[PDB]
Length: 99
Image (cartoon, rainbow, N blue to C red; front, side, top):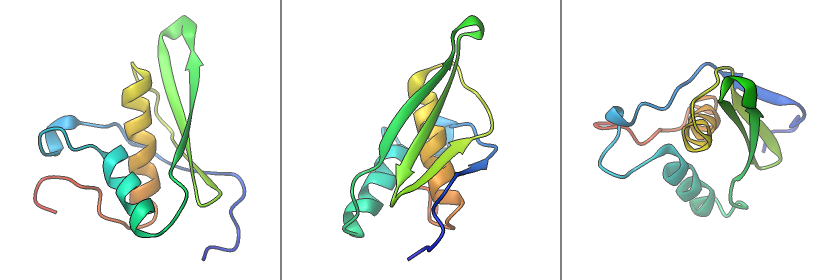
């Protein structure tokens, strides 16, 4: 239900685990959303700038790609950021404390 799914949607996000309950992450919130929606589960591809020890991640959900504009220090932190981009750009709840 989102006709044009080309390209990449981006926002400027970094995952800050202090905003989340113990051991709940955007990846889990997004995965549960896909399951609730009977959607294929998210697919993450890592991007690297190894000379800077930087990481980015592109997540595909319902054929649309999402990615943060910002780089991070680890594959896992970048994957969390990509999940946030996917949720926040759609207006969905992100799983934070008191949301």
